[PDB]
Image 1 (cartoon, rainbow, N blue to C red):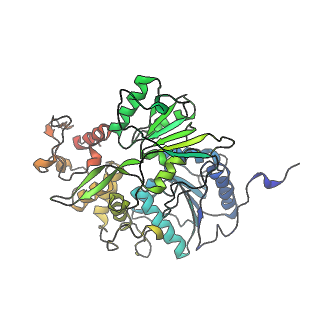
Image 2 (spheres, rainbow, N blue to C red; image 1 turned 60 degrees about the vertical axis):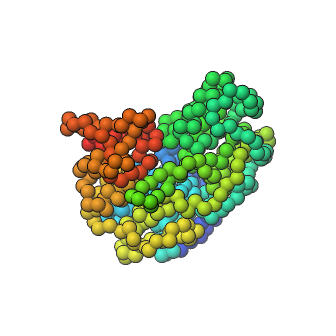
Length: 442
């Protein structure tokens, strides 16, 4: 009645060590849908200890289903295939205890430029090139590409227009007057609330995917019936919503390490996104079946020197600390080597400081740069003194009101961290978490 052609045809040598397969599976295809289960089951058949890396908590679910029925361990008791987020795996790589000797590693959405993704990618490529494993990077925008308008499935109407930046009292029609299938990418959360409010005071109720709430409001994109989507950079990694068109002003904020007086991390004002990033934003459409009326409205042009972004040095701080049987430090994935020009091992710490470094990132929720400086200074995880003893220039304020901290010990102190990383206080939700850290309740 039927041929086993029910499940895809997985070429061979994609499991052959010393090889790195780049699956440029354009969006909407059978990427996680069918391609993965096929490859996974085939490995489980080939008796291969496997590792599956998901970019986000949400994408981890998209894979739990496509893999629902297969022997896999998530986040009996003797499975041979693991599945966790990028960050979780990289954290474990910093542990003094070696990870399993995976014969095959598959990374989903392998373009995410977060420090951890960059580190894991370096680790994986080093493993395949050593001959200890075979790797597979799954992404339509692989590191190195710069194509803002690449092939797609559904016809895309590419045309530039004047996308507003904030609240408007009049003008622009295609905005407040449309079908209701469009995604709007914005630079900051501060600005995302205005363009959002405006769409509310007009004639539409949309959803705001916050910087760190993608694992709550996303699910609602499936059908909570809305006209527009207001996200930030985060959507670019495993986000699927309802839309026939997308508004893309090609803007974003990005962490930068300054070096004037004290070294500090700033979030540089709204700047151009990367080409691959631009694609990713447009790729949210033109990936559907029969549809033909899917247009892309973009303002501004993209740039390619994302080199001053803190993530490259931060990914390096993680790699110099990766524990490897030989002791030879993992290099970065071939196409990303040229982003940082630092000596291999300039950031390697000693056993006890490395653990603190890890803890400050896992239990403290602090960015890589900040946790490294704190650990590098010999400070202990529990010792929060550094949160109040910085110079006068590091006092944090809301409107002009100096923020104070009620420690769980009873005192009321002014928030003045010794090292300043703006990622810890720009977004109110982040400031909240950090306050909890400074108070000693974490």
